[PDB]
Image 1 (cartoon, helix red, strand yellow):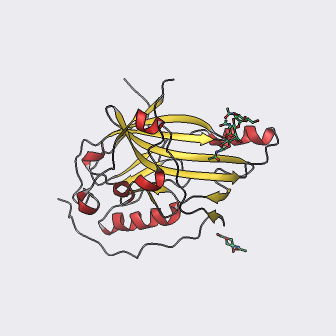
Image 2: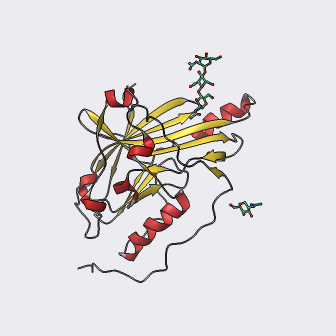
Image 3: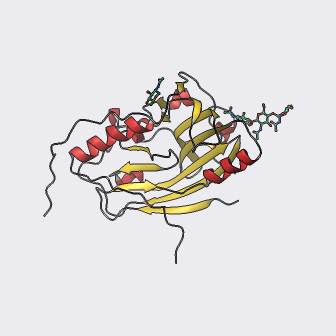
Length: 241
Ligand SMILES: *[C@@H]1O[C@H](CO)[C@@H](O[C@@H]2O[C@H](CO)[C@@H](O[C@@H]3O[C@H](CO)[C@@H](O)[C@H](O)[C@H]3NC(C)=O)[C@H](O)[C@H]2NC(C)=O)[C@H](O)[C@H]1NC(C)=O
Ligand SMILES: *[C@@H]1O[C@H](CO)[C@@H](O)[C@H](O)[C@H]1NC(C)=O
């Protein structure tokens, strides 16, 4: 019978970033609709309730930057958005804008970034993978089950991936079941609100730590309750009969 206790650990790490960039603060904008061949679907589940969950689908961004270098492109730009898809509506989860990026280097080497805009509930237990293209969730509560949509924009061109998240082991004893005032994900918006430009990022989401520190803060909380961070997160499975 495995104990359910806090454990000693070092404070959250302060990693050195990959590179120096200018952070663009206090920007807003309408988040594009997530709706409308069809979308590549993947599946993510956890064998144990206090496991880490990954949402991983290599989007082949390496090739599309290689394509741009072959056309002598001087730069590229990018936007990464996550949503929770429900009946009729979508919750915005994550927004991140990369501008003036170098295509000869690996994705993300950009002269300008916004901070990542996060849903407040989600940011307490989840952070982007190291390549900033997937998500890691640290022992999510069962209420996290659902359909998560990733939208990758390169040079204005979007590509979508869905993740069907299934959590049959239930809550973990230390899962975060709410943020302040018990709030869970933020408001679900229907397609029309997105189209009419009402889902302003600075209004519904909050600017947050870059991936290195974000991973460090959550990993610390996760580890202090006994969790082990895996050394690798494999690609999420597709549909299998
Ligand atoms: C990331 O870069 C994208 C392009 O690299 C930007 O999207 C492009 O913005 C252009 C404006 O500079 C659009 O302009 C088109 O060109 C003529 C002018 O010659 C206009 O009159 C047209 O009306 C206009 N056409 C269209 C189809 O809008 C580009 O078309 C547009 N291209 C794409 C593929 O979106 C993004 O704005 C930029 N993203 C960010 C966040 O800065
Ligand atoms: C730029 O930042 C990198 C890491 O972020 C650091 O190693 C380097 O010393 C910095 N250089 C300057 C000139 O700021």
